[PDB]
Every structure is written in structure tokens, then in C-alpha cells.
Amino acid sequence: MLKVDTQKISPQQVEAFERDGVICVKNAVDDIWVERMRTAVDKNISIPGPLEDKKPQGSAEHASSIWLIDADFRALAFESPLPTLAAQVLKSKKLNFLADGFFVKKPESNGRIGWHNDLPYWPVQGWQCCKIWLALDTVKQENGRLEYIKGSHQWGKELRERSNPSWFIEPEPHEILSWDMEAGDCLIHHFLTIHHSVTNISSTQRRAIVTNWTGDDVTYYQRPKAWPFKPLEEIDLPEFNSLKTKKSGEPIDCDIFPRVQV
Ligand code: NI
Image 1 (cartoon, helix red, strand yellow):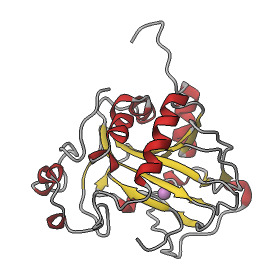
Image 2: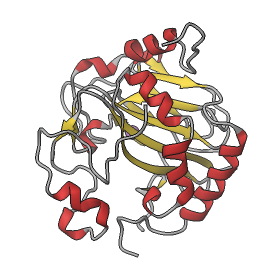
Image 3: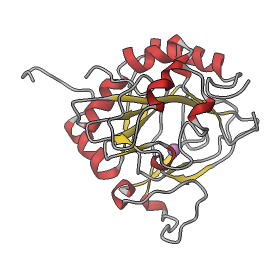
Image 4: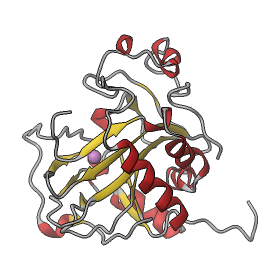
């Protein structure tokens, strides 16, 4: 550490992430990255993802693991500022890229994604897990923004969407955090922070790229109904060979969950 070092995430923002479970980073990537990823999203939104067989309409267009086939998604994960931001908020010395994806709400056909946190969808366990949600369009409320229950990552509770457990009380409006965003801004949220996203009622699409990241204290855990949402034997891609031979408790590191420079 040098006396001249500056970090994109201020120490106060690092502390806000721990307190609230979510922060917003303005200008997370520059406009060159924005244009490159707009093209990559527009290219991949029309086809099933690498893990699907080449379609029912959801509340958003979504696929995962685009970096396996697309060099621009791969470059965003490994060459852009995003892995540096993830390392800064997790405060970890190791960093794994867990998965990428897109979520696009098209005005013709989208809807609300209900209250949930992300942990129950991923075969991991441990505190240092976060999602970076990179906006590629203007995102205010009318555009289908995300909103968060402040501090809910500290509750120690998993919430699958529409699971309706008795402990979960609908939040009061003043308990809900959100931001206005422009293309290139990102949200970074903890895997236990409960969030939802409202309907895009605007005339323009709401494109976002997601990257998921894990740090020092995380291990593999084959919880039910988690990504990749199908038996591993049904996936032929070589990156998954190293995951098939992995057992719970072991570090995440493998070809599908690769280590990234810190
Ligand atoms: Ni989510």
C-alpha cells in the first residue's frame, strides 16, 4: 500500500456496503465499455445462453455464462474495472469470478421480479459474495429499477423469490433504498441483501449486465435448485469438468469459477 493510492470505492462507501448491503458506484466503467457491452447484450439477447438448449417469456430477458462464448463478456469480467470494484467491497485478498449474465426489461413484455436475495440461487456458502449490476441505460423508477431492504443482508435469512416464509414482513417505504442511475453506473449488493425490481413502464429498454464475485471465506455448497439449475451431467462444456469433481467445503477455484487478479 502506497501513500498515493486511491480507490474507486471510498472507505465510506466500503462502510456503507457493510451497513446497508448495497452501494451505487457512479461511472463504474467508461463509455467505451458501455458501448462495447451494449453491442454484446444486443447480440446475445436473441439466443439461448450457453447452458440452455437451442424461451418462455419471463419478467426480464435473462441468460447466464455469456463469457464462455462471447469475448466481450469475457473482457468485461477480466479486463474492466469490475473485478477491482468487487475486491474493494469484499475486502478480500483472493477473488473468484462466479458467473455473469444479463437482465433486460423490454417495454413490450416485462414485469416485477419480487423480493428475494441471491444466495439461495448459487452453490456457494460464505459471507464474501456480491453481485455487480452494471446499467447500460438510464434507470430511474419508471425504467424498472432495483430497490433494496436496507441492512437485510445482516438478517441471516435466505429468501427465494415468491417463497413467502412467515418471518418476512413487507417493508415500509422508508426502509427501501434505491438510486437514479445512468449507463456505466453500477449497483453492488451482498448475496443476502433482499431486493426486487419494478416494472419497466418506459418506452426504452433497460439493459443490465451482472457479474457475481466471491472472496476469501467462500466454499462450494450444492444447495438444491441452485445455478446452473440443471444436473452437471447435462452440461458438456469443458469448464464444468473441474466442477464435477468438486465437493462441498472446498474452495470455489475451478475453470468455471476462475480466480482473478487482485
Ligand atoms: Ni437478485
